Amino acid sequence: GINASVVNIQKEIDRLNEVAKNLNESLIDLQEL
Amino acid sequence: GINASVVNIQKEIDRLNEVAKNLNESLIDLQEL
Amino acid sequence: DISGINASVVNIQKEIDRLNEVAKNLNESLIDLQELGK
Amino acid sequence: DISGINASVVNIQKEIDRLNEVAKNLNESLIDLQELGK
Ligand SMILES: [Cl-]
Image (cartoon, rainbow over all chains, first blue to last red; front, side, top):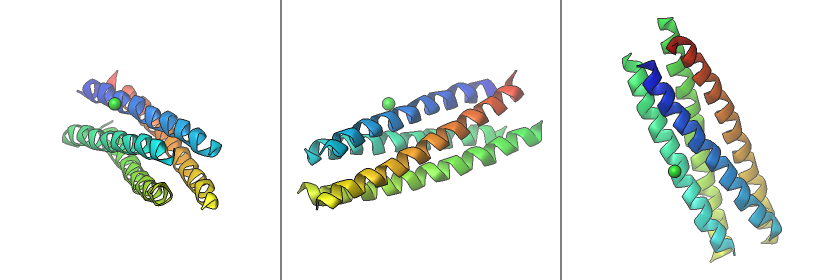
């Protein structure tokens, strides 16, 4: 119930953290240019 | 160069759009509860 | 506690709205970089 | 146009900051839902 949504939202927070991390890696690539 | 970062950022925008879409699906699951 | 579910729906909705605004801005930066790129 | 790369770095940095703030808020909503959940 609520637990199904807790699992699904946790997955999305994990996905969102990957977005931020990977954008940061691109920022370093660009900062260097 | 810039093209490598354009590809990598596009991938992250695609990932971010999945975050928003999937959170919205969980919101519907919760709104219904 | 049912007030609780409604509160979290409203809260998460606000975050989705902010994610959508981020995605719009990132798409704009992508265009900016393409203009440098080609 | 080099000003251009720097501008996009600053712009994307602002968006990463906003994503990090979203993630913090979503983590808080996750805790709220867990409190309903268990
Ligand atoms: Cl993924």
